[PDB]
Amino acid sequence: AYFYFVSFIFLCSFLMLNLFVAVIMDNFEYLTRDSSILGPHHLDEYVR
Amino acid sequence: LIIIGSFFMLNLVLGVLSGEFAKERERVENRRAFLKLRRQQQIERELN
Amino acid sequence: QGGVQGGMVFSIYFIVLTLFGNYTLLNVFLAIAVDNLANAQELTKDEQ
Amino acid sequence: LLTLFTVSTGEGWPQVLKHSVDATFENQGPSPGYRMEMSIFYVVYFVVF
Amino acid sequence: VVRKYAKKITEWPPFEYMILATIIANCIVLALEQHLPDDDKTPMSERLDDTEPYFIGIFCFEAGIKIIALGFSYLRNGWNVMDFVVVLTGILATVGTEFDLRTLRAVRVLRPLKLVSGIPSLQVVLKSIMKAMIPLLQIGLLLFFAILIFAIIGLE
Amino acid sequence: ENALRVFNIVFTSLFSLECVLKVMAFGILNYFRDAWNIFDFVTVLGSITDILVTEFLSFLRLFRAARLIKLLRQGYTIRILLWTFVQSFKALPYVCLLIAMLFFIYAIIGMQVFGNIGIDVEDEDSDEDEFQITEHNN
Amino acid sequence: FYWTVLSLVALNTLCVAIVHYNQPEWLSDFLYYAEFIFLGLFMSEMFIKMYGLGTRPYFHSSFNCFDCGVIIGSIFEVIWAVIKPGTSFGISVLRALRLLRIFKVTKYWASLRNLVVSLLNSMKSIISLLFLLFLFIVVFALLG
Amino acid sequence: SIALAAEDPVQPNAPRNNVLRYFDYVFTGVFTFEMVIKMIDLGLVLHQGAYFRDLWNILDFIVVSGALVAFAFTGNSKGKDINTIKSLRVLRVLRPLKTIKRLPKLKAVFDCVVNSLKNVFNILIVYMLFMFIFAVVAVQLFKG
Amino acid sequence: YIQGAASPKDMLILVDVSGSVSGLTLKLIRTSVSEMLETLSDDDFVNVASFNSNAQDVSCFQHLVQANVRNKKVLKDAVNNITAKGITDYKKGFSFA
Ligand SMILES: CC(C)CCC[C@@H](C)[C@H]1CC[C@H]2[C@@H]3CC=C4C[C@@H](OC(=O)CCC(=O)O)CC[C@]4(C)[C@H]3CC[C@]12C
Ligand SMILES: CC(C)CCC[C@@H](C)[C@H]1CC[C@H]2[C@@H]3CC=C4C[C@@H](OC(=O)CCC(=O)O)CC[C@]4(C)[C@H]3CC[C@]12C
Ligand SMILES: CC(C)CCC[C@@H](C)[C@H]1CC[C@H]2[C@@H]3CC=C4C[C@@H](OC(=O)CCC(=O)O)CC[C@]4(C)[C@H]3CC[C@]12C
Ligand SMILES: CC(C)CCC[C@@H](C)[C@H]1CC[C@H]2[C@@H]3CC=C4C[C@@H](O)CC[C@]4(C)[C@H]3CC[C@]12C
Ligand SMILES: CC(C)CCC[C@@H](C)[C@H]1CC[C@H]2[C@@H]3CC=C4C[C@@H](O)CC[C@]4(C)[C@H]3CC[C@]12C
Ligand SMILES: CC(C)CCC[C@@H](C)[C@H]1CC[C@H]2[C@@H]3CC=C4C[C@@H](O)CC[C@]4(C)[C@H]3CC[C@]12C
Ligand SMILES: [Ca+2]
């Protein structure tokens, strides 16, 4: 039970963290966007 | 409730903060401090 | 402060403390880690 | 290391802190609030890890 | 709100250091207080409590110097506004007791924050922290909506 | 309780008119090509269902509780931020699968090793910290 | 010399880890004397560098100053034990931080050294950040 | 994998476990057949295409070998040694991991996780050294 | 045993009822005072007083009463109905005792 729970907390936190960075770093262009420079988010304003 | 409320919001908070920190690094005043740091290190290597 | 009958307005002290404290700690320590590690990566790449 | 790992995950450390401040001497029982300066150990531990 | 310019005298470096010292002393005095149940006081409580006139007088004096020198650009700075309300609430409780004024003592907790106003270096660092959490407010709006929706569902 | 229930009948009527009004204006087919329109249509159909049964449980009216989401479209920066992150979770399905396997492997190991522990044990001592393997947690 | 003193630190790090609640009496006697032996060797290692490299070159080195602090701290503990028996802080374990110098032989030294270089560069900012964080705790503590 | 999830832990002699036991024979049989042909197509000896060279092949080898050995102990006498056979039955939980190698995109995600461990390994060693120092100090303070 | 272990007493219990004894300490004080009253014979005289800032008698008794089975009941009932509020003044409670 010592190894069962101690390893789980490490592995669960590590695998969840890799999920977070994968989702974050997929949208990293949007998160570091600047309103001055053109971006894909702006182009939807052209459509309406 | 836990997945949406706690794990999904934590993902956005890390995502938004990380994007802000990337933009802050490339600020003109912040870049100049790093350029001073790089030059000061180059002197130390040659001086040694 | 009374009980459930009269002291329910005092939960705001605890809500504000844990809500602000949770993300203030994240902001302070993650900014320290990101900025200093990003400096080290650029500083290492430049010397190579 | 197992006790500190439990504190790192954040669960149950208030009880570990209570036992730490109440400790008196080797092979002797606890006394409430004996060593209240041992709180510095857990505050410094949280800052680092 | 002054008599225009008439021998207006400004500050000199030891002045703000004396203000800093009195703020630190006030913080220590606040940290030395013990609260006991049901209208019970410790012997040191009276000695600590009688020091309040001195601190409030010093703070009122420095606020007066700044307000006459600047001319009431005093309230332009956000830090001075926080200083002004600290002085105002103190005088109401300290001078006169006819109204219920035990609640106004709670405003004294903000006095340690005057360290940030006094030391300009801390202001720059404090600006950095608040700047990053401006985007995070939009996350809080998502969080509140999520809590509201799940509260309705839990209510049903 | 009756007054609250009466207001439900008033709203579910008006919310049914919007669907009727849009369908005629947009057309049978074009209207049914927008995700919100079906979401709106299933919501009105679910709520109207329960009302007739009462005179002739309504947890599917909590779909109506989801109507508040429509207010998000007015706030732009929230809508883009919420939508982009949701799309990213769809583009990373196998990363979620790896977490599911970790729970699977650690669940099977737990059943075989720690499954036999008894839970019926209870005593006046009731050292709750001592015994955390109970009817709910096992 | 560099590898030999480093191997001594590994022995000293091992010695302070053996201690447990009921250790046999022979173990306590061995460890009691071994601390003085290790302390003596590292103080001598201090003096050899001091005379070998000169007092000014030795002290100006950042690494050697850290060795001074643990050496001075170790002396403080032993005298403290006699005056007030019952309390031991194990200050000698801080000598184990010298094991991080092993990273020099690997390719990973540049990444690790640069991180410490950048941390020391912004030491003023980090200290101010912790102070402001401490101030808000005090305000909330006073409000409570 | 689904069979391992249906099994009743509380009742060793449950009717469900009796039925599922027959299924365990078939699944091992399939894994035995694929093992030998993989040894036949490749080579056991280390000729740079060795079957034992690939790490997952050892993982496949362990699952099938444990199942076969568990049968041998049960074969002689059903309940002569319940402890070790119960331990060997636990190795079946490695069956889901056999999916990672075969699925291309699941292997790719797995390599990314291992890649992240490599980057943070150097800091992880520093983390444990610092945590070791705190543990030794904590022992001296609160031992006994 | 109590009869043979000592001589008749003139006991005056002085109970502190300032604010700081509020909560658990008050329950322990009342239980302790009752248990002390149980160790008194009819040859013993007892009176219970209390003081936060001015001393007063807890019950109707004003001077000293022998520890009957009924005087003791009156004192116990009076003790079980005291509340903690004020600032301790030892020089006014001891001057009363
Ligand atoms: C984010 C970080 C930088 C802030 C952490 C706050 C610390 C500066 C505080 C939190 C707990 C405090 C400790 C809590 C308890 C005590 C015991 C107390 O010392 C006594 O002997 C008092 C006797 C008693 O209280 O019975 C006062 C100092 C000390 C070590 C305090 C010192 C200041 C500490 C470490
Ligand atoms: C830097 C690292 C690699 C150092 C080596 C690890 C040590 C910190 C650990 C590893 C195993 C530990 C040991 C595991 C178990 C025991 C048995 C324990 O003895 C008893 O339980 C009873 C002794 C008796 O009654 O005689 C004493 C401590 C000791 C040696 C431990 C001391 C600390 C040890 C050596
Ligand atoms: C999520 C993925 C991995 C698939 C889900 C797997 C398990 C969560 C499911 C699959 C088959 C299910 C089992 C199918 C049939 C039964 C019998 C059913 O009947 C009984 O009460 C026991 C039989 C008896 O009393 O004799 C109890 C639930 C159980 C064990 C089910 C428990 C949940 C199981 C193991
Ligand atoms: C895997 C090992 C290292 C520990 C497991 C990680 C989890 C359980 C631990 C490690 C780091 C911890 C968090 C680190 C950051 C903070 C600071 C503040 O925001 C709230 C506390 C909080 C949230 C800690 C709570 C629990 C925490 C998330
Ligand atoms: C950063 C690395 C070097 C970690 C080493 C620092 C740690 C181990 C030190 C720093 C401050 C220290 C504390 C300072 C003061 C006291 C009070 C004393 O009566 C008991 C020990 C105790 C509670 C110390 C325990 C050890 C301690 C927490
Ligand atoms: C091959 C995969 C699908 C494994 C699935 C096996 C599952 C679905 C089957 C196999 C054996 C089956 C069990 C066999 C034994 C019993 C006891 C019987 O009195 C009731 C049904 C019950 C409880 C069956 C439930 C379903 C069951 C568990
Ligand atoms: Ca008192």
Image (spheres, rainbow, N blue to C red):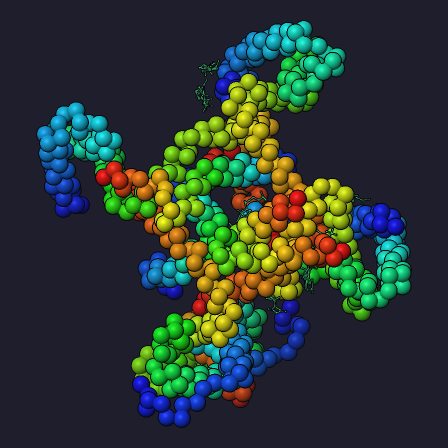
Q: Residue at x 63, y 36 (%)?
A: H118
In the image shown, does I62 or H86 lie closer to the viewer? H86
Farthest residue, direction bottom: E7
Q: Give x and y (percent) for residue F5.
A: 16, 42
Quarter of the image for residue H112 reads top right
Q: Give x and y (percent) for residue F105.
A: 55, 27
In the image shown, does F75 or C44 lie closer to the viewer? C44
Q: Give x and y (percent) for residue H90.
A: 62, 23
Quarter of the image for residue G86 reads bottom right
From this viewpoint, is residue H34 visible? Answer: yes
Q: Is residue H11 above or below residue G142?
A: above
> On the picture, is F9 further left or further right than I39?
left
Q: Residue at x 45, y 86 (%)?
A: E10
Q: Is residue I52 above or below residue E152?
A: below
Of the four image quadrants, the one with ligand 3 is: top left
Q: Quadrant of the C terminus of chain A?
A: top left
